[PDB]
Structure formats: structure tokens, C-alpha cells
Image (cartoon, rainbow, N blue to C red; front, side):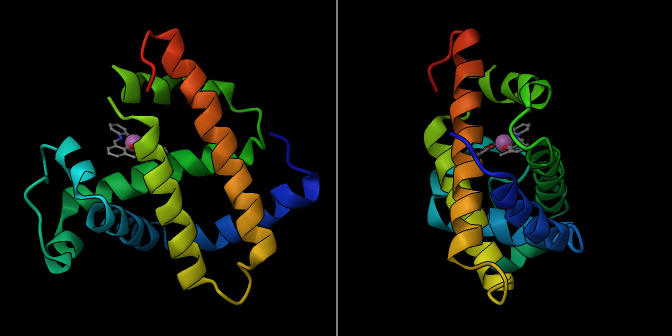
Length: 152
Ligand SMILES: Cc1cccc(/C=N/c2ccccc2/N=C/c2cccc(C)c2O)c1O
Ligand SMILES: [Cr+3]
């Protein structure tokens, strides 16, 4: 997978907006993920019993994880593909098990929330670029998974 500098700028331009409210975007993304694919919530022993969106919105553990996710992903995206240093530790956290299928689910949630919150600028071009960036992310982290003996 390869993105042009222009495509990377579309990704970083929308991410700058995410950075204006990391906690909020994080809550929206995780809630979308958990409601769409409930099995993913089972991976979090600290808040796997949350059910209503109200409870999810009031959860500090969920909010903190959302911030962790967006902060880490933001660092990865800013590397514009040269993210080996960032994927190594993340693979450690995900493969010692978060399957590729779950990464696809959260990628879908990210695209959905970005479009919902920034429809004026997050169009087909930006969505396509973000999709490529997340696809690259999943492909490369899968490689890291395999180095640890996990197929994902
Ligand atoms: C996508 C992404 C970007 C940056 C950071 C993370 C961190 N993930 C985790 C870190 C520590 C422990 C668990 C993590 N991920 C848990 C997880 C659970 C269900 C579904 C998905 C999909 C997950 O990534 C992350 O998942
Ligand atoms: Cr994770």
C-alpha cells in the first residue's frame, strides 16, 4: 500500500480535527465499535459489563482507552507509513489477542465517526485516503503479529 503526500495530508488534516476533542472522538469510536460488534467489548475486563450508551459515556475506563487509542494511532498516521517503531510496541499489547478482524471493525468505526463529525471536509477523497492508511496499518501490524507467532 502506498499513499501520495497529498493523500497523507488529507489524513493529517482530518486528524487535526480529531485532536481538538480526542476524548470525545474516542468515546464515539469505541461506543460505535462495541455496539456494532459486542464481542469486542469482552476484551476489556475493566468495563465489559457496560451496556447502555449512557453507561459507556460515563465510563472513565472507556474514555481513557479511547484517548490511548487515538493518541497512539495519531502518532502512527503522522509517520506517513514509516511506523515500524510505533507498531512494534502495539503488536506487543495486541498479540501477547486482538485479531485482524477486530482491527477492521475499529477501522470501520473510525471512518464512520469521522464522517459523522466532519462531513463538510471528510469526503470520498479523505475517506479513501484514511481507508488506505488504516489498511496499511492493519497489514503491517499483522506482520508484527506473525513475528510473535500470532496469525491474528
Ligand atoms: C487501533 C489501536 C491504535 C492504537 C492503540 C491501540 C491499543 N490497543 C490496546 C492497548 C492495550 C491493550 C489492549 C488494546 N486493544 C484492545 C482491543 C480490544 C478489542 C478490539 C480492538 C480493536 C482492540 O484494539 C489500538 O487498538
Ligand atoms: Cr487496541
